[PDB]
Image (cartoon, rainbow, N blue to C red):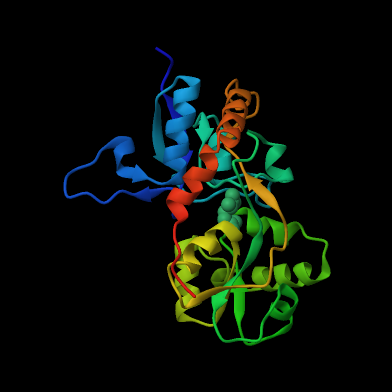
């Protein structure tokens, strides 16, 4: 039998979530969401079973001062996992160190805040001094600001970096709590904003999308699965299955 593939992933609504049950769940049965459905589809097409393992450090992945990576990216580089099936953003810096599939979903960074302010854009947000802002530590939004040569974004990075202890949150859930409970705006991917703002009517997107990019399945460089995965993703795309999966996990339809 084909060796069981090790899948690195991360908890993120509605991509990967704990299933609610009144009875014990083990292994993969503990999880549900868009990425679990994607895995079910991909594994059918490619002919494997798999073992879902949450990334031990709970990070997506970024490189430090010394050039060392962490998170799911590190798991792939170190061949601790065969695949990363998660909302893993396809970026230039990452693509140099792992092999991504073609994208299964598109998105862009935008702003999540409460309602009622005159802040209408990143420019507004960077200029004002009332509201703090940041991003998930060691994810692609953080790295976007870190690498930016756009003046407003350079300022925003200097600010986030200066206030890193507080401004850079552990995960999206903690960032949402910080938005709700303090004067803080979260720089968050638009698909995640879409999800949360249709469920919590106290939240809103501010401004438009600041960039445009995709989520892809990650594999270690040289993986024999990456191209097979790309082909499977395109099949699912063309068959309308990716669209259906998005409708299943995002619907409805929740706030004015
Ligand atoms: N999808 C991002 C994590 C979320 C974010 O950075 O806003 C990543 O792959 O690193």
Residue 171 versus residue 1 in the image, above or below: below
Query: Taking the image as drawn, is residue 138 in sight?
Result: no
> What quarter of the picture does the N terminus occupy?
top left
Q: Give the residue drawn at x 40%, y 36%.
A: 52
Q: Give the residue drawn at x 69%, y 67%.
A: 208
Taking the view exactly as shown, the residue that stands out farthest to the top is: 1
Residue 227 versus residue 241 in the image, above or below: above
Q: Give the residue drawn at x 72%, y 58%.
A: 211
| Residue 125: quadrant of the picture | bottom right
Q: Report x, y in % for residue 170.
A: 49, 61
In the rendered view, does 224 fall on the left or right side of 91?
left
Query: Taking the image as drawn, is residue 2 in sight?
Result: yes
Q: Report x, y in % for residue 209.
A: 69, 63
| Residue 43: quadrant of the picture | top left
- Total labels drawn: 0
Image region (quadrant) for ligand 1: bottom right
**Most foreground residue, 21 or 238:** 238
Q: Report x, y in % for residue 226.
A: 61, 27
Q: Report x, y in % for residue 100.
A: 64, 35
In the rendered view, does 105 fall on the left or right side of 47?
right
Taking the view exactly as shown, the residue that stands out farthest to the left is: 23
């Amino acid at each position: 039998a084909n060796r069981t593939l090790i899948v690195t992933t991360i908890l993120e609504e509605p991509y990967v979530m704990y299933r609610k049950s009144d009875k014990p769940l083990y292994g993969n049965d503990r999880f549900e969401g868009y990425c679990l459905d994607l895995l079910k589809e991909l594994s059918n097409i490619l002919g494997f079973i798999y073992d879902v393992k949450l990334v031990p450090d709970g990070k997506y992945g970024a490189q430090n001062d010394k050039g060392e990576w962490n998170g799911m990216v590190k798991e792939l580089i170190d061949h601790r996992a065969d695949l990363a099936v998660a909302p893993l953003t396809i970026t230039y810096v990452r693509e140099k160190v792992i092999d991504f599939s073609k994208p299964f979903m598109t998105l862009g960074i935008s702003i999540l805040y409460r309602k009622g302010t005159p802040i209408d854009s990143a420019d507004d947000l960077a200029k004002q001094t009332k509201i703090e802002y940041g991003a998930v530590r060691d994810g692609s939004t953080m790295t976007f600001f870190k690498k930016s040569k756009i003046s407003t974004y350079e300022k925003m990075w200097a600010f986030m970096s200066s206030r890193q202890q507080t401004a850079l949150v552990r995960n999206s859930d903690e960032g949402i709590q910080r938005v709700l409970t303090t004067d803080y705006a979260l720089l968050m991917e638009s698909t995640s904003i879409e999800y949360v703002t249709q469920r919590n009517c106290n939240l809103t997107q501010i401004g438009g999308l600041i960039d445009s990019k995709g989520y892809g399945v990650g594999t270690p460089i040289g993986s024999p699965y990456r191209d097979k995965i790309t082909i499977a993703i395109l099949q699912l795309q063309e068959e309308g299955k990716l669209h259906m999966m998005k409708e299943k996990w995002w619907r409805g339809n929740g706030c004015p």
